[PDB]
Image: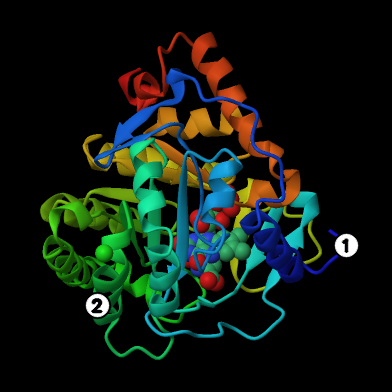
Amino acid sequence: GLLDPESAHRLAVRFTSLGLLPRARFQDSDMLEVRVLGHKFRNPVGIAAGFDKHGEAVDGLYKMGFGFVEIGSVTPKPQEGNPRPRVFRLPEDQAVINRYGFNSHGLSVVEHRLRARQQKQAKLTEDGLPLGVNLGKNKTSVDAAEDYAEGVRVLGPLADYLVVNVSSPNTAGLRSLQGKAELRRLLTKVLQERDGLRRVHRPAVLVKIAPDLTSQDKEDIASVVKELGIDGLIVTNTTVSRPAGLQGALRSETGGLSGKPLRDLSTQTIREMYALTQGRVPIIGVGGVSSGQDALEKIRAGASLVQLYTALTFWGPPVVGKVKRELEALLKEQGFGGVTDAIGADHRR
Ligand SMILES: Cc1cc2nc3c(=O)[nH]c(=O)nc-3n(C[C@H](O)[C@H](O)[C@H](O)COP(=O)(O)O)c2cc1C
Ligand SMILES: O=C(O)c1cc(=O)[nH]c(=O)[nH]1
Ligand SMILES: [Cl-]
């Protein structure tokens, strides 16, 4: 916290990549295993997109004890992102605001990085540690569908799941892709491209949505997802809202807000999306998770898996084991046999 947040992030990625931090001691219980999206997940706690944008620290992140890793967002061509400053800590709120704008090494660079460890990843996936790849679009793209299609073609063969990220608040016009007609067109093309890949290279496709959607938006997304047979949802990205009560000096910076102020907004979005999809569409729940309780609330709301990022920036690597240990204890306390039993449990009350 003695460096600016962006410099701190860069060093964190570097240290993680090099495997400098200690191997996680917490051994995952059978209670934490989830089978979803055609894969086994040794535990349901993943690293959210944005920490490892360019796929530089995948192995280090598994070493940290994450049950799955999502890299990205990756754009077709390299791009620098928005001018600095573009990331801000709100310590009083346990929150971050960012406006990176999809800084990305681009598909080619990431493709080569993942190819260098493709067989290692195949073994990790087999051993219950899958890899997700989150796709974005270039700033000056005229056809968003073509950007996402290129992402499917290039990184789809290297991923257990792909994420169509239409919910960054930091790319002009992007979140209009969540609209029914735009989303149907975009996802039809994405699924067509995915279906064209050889079977062993054919990933699940998820859509990552905003926490800022209207009821109509959410109904429309649920409809499209079901119509097209989309494999899952990631719920949610950062919020452009600024909840009453934020204390951080930097609360009025432009960008997506993450961390504790997003937590319950995200949980409620999960709850709504689960109900709108009749519990038949896997949800990865993300936003403000820093404890076992936070994880379980999202799971009971309908998430099959959870992710965190912002908590890691406050609590450091120990937060991963802490979430897992606390989640295990709570499942036992509440009479669940395991994570699987708790998924969507609130809806069966
Ligand atoms: C600095 C930063 C960068 C992010 N970059 C991305 C990104 O490139 N793609 C994406 O889909 N989400 C991105 N996110 C959103 C996270 O994946 C996550 O949805 C959100 O931060 C809520 O989780 P958290 O409260 O645990 O951080 C980013 C978040 C932060 C804080
Ligand atoms: O600016 C980014 O790259 C970015 C930030 C964020 O919160 N979410 C996202 O999808 N991208
Ligand atoms: Cl390949």
Task: Choose the circle earlier in sequence order: 2 or 1.
Answer: 1
User: Which element is circle 2 on?
Assistant: helix
Q: Name the residue beneath numbered marker 1.
A: 2
- Residue 63 in picture, x, y percent from top left: 58, 42
Where is residue 154? Give x, y as percent: 29, 72
Q: How is the image coloured?
A: rainbow
122 displayed left or right of 66: left
Drawn side of residue 175 relative to residue 245, left or right: left
Asked if 119 appears above or below 349 in the picture, the reply is: below
Quadrant of res 190: bottom left
Residue 112: x and y, percent? Answer: 41, 72
Q: Nearer the viewer, residue 255 or 162?
A: 162
Q: Residues within 10 Å of mark 1 (few under 14, many from 20)?
A: few
Q: Please, what is the three-letter code of the amino acid marked with disc 1?
A: Leu
The three-letter amino acid code for the residue at tag 2 is: Ala
Residue 127 quadrant: top left
Q: Residue at x 72, y 45 (%)?
A: 316
Depth order, front residue of 249/279? 279
Q: Residue furthest right?
A: 2
* Residue at figure coordinates x 84%, y 58% from the top left: 1
Q: Image point 51% across, 69% down: which residue?
A: 54
Q: Nearer the viewer, residue 275 or 119?
A: 119
Asked whether residue 312 appears in the rendered view, the answer is yes
Tell me which image quadrant ligand 1 sits in. bottom right
